[PDB]
Length: 287
Image: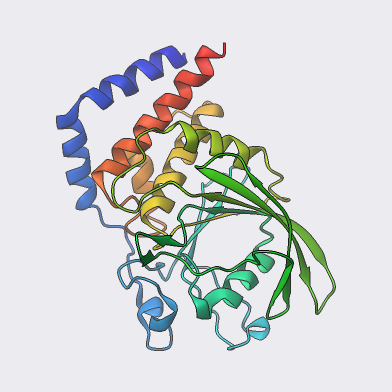
């Protein structure tokens, strides 16, 4: 029953001492292993937006060195899996820097990715969160990846959708890609409703995802909002398959085994649980 599981989450949400104790336990959570030595190496420091938010050595996206303009494998990006391969995978990554824009697109190309989730505005009260990695109009060429803005649909003030035609100009292969851009999510504190994000999520998940390809999810540090989104999606997707592991804190633990520090605040943790419960509610009210 969803009525049973929804009753559980609502009790969980009202229980602020349980919340505080889960979060405390999560602040002390440490993966094994947890080394980020390659990311911290001297060549790579300039390629990270935030020094505290890095991929683990055991779980990082490796660019194909021969295809890289700088001949490096490094991008601040982490694969996030389940053990089952039939389940939805992600790449959690930082918002591209000006000098990592060609790295980002090489990652998009080699991963197979047809969906990008962007969770930040480019600038948040005067603080730059992300560099623009897409053309505002027409086409832009980043190394060998020609990105063509086909369509922009503003659905509301909370979110819009860009559709792109992507060409590898070397091989002449083509791909369609959709960027889902959420505009209204602050880096500190949460959105006052979970509604618009959940509507946004329904549009993301109905999009053509590719043949077993990751969704790329990013914000600024690729940890705070990125993690909170991936947590909500992961919990809800598991529920839909009727998976028996229904524990949000343990699910967050599974995400932090793969990229460190995801979900940055207790507010984001509590928002995630509120969003999961609002979606379950919504599904039932439609039945």
